Length: 18
Length: 305
Length: 24
Length: 78
Image (tube, rainbow over all chains, first blue to last red; front, side, top):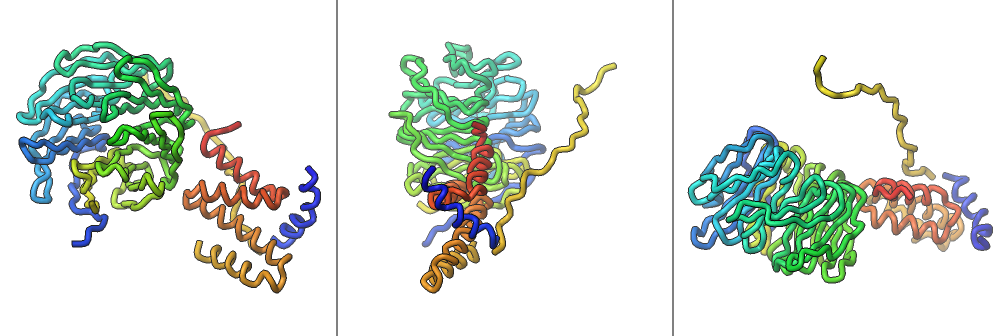
């Protein structure tokens, strides 16, 4: 999944502050 | 005179025990609307809707175990009922006498349906066949096999082409009445289907299951027209409006929901009932809804036309 | 030696995984 | 429902001030609203919202698990 690996940082940012 | 959804009458302690079925029929010659209810207290009761009031006319007995289904004829003044002991009884609504009885063994005769001509009774069976009994004959003329499990609900299309059946595994089966051949076998749901119905034009098939979902099918192609949700528990009964643009459903969550088939959205919900609402039906012209449930109550709801 | 057929089971069924709304 | 919709509206309204932060705030609020729709038995809207989240944020595990839970609730265990 090429697009998935680019979104790892964004999802980590989302979850870091939940 | 603006018309809005709202309760109009409420008969408390209608039966000793839970009311498990209802049926609304309109008779032209008598010009009096009739309601037939069956209950787990082994009693059938015939009420007349007049002057915005329910008045008991007959109280018919004979069923051994709970009465599971009660139906009326669209033209004749006849009614039918089935009990948990698989006994079927025909009642003359004019005099309140038992026309005849059919002993369907220990397993057959779960739920009843009147054919459009009111010349037959269709009932699902434990083995997986829909047996057909002559109203005048009183005998099993033949049966259509599904090769499935317990059939919980049965329906007759108003035009008489097909009779539908819903199984305990969620599978739907549509038979052609003319040739008695299994037209379609659809996946349907994964939980038991306790009630399915046809549209007044026989174009749509609406089925209800324990998963809380109401599925619409186009019988012509047997394709899934849509899925409706909003009930918090089992859906126990569905019934189409005469206007053909609406239908009503009931559920274990103590609510009766009226859905619009066009917009596929629940247009109203009644929370009056205090227990499982087992039956819901429309009147002849679609301006009333009758509902019955485990709280032993009969509720009438007005509806705009 | 006749009675209602019912096997009594002492069950310990865990709750489903919680999925409450998240706080930011 | 009112507050979740207001939160989504507010995050959208003030997104220009900081798009990156408000996008993540809206993602969490959107998941909350989908979970609410599940609560209100609007499983079609909840499923559509979960899929919308998953389409843009394929790393949101909770959305996958909610779709699976809804499928299991439907009775489709596969």
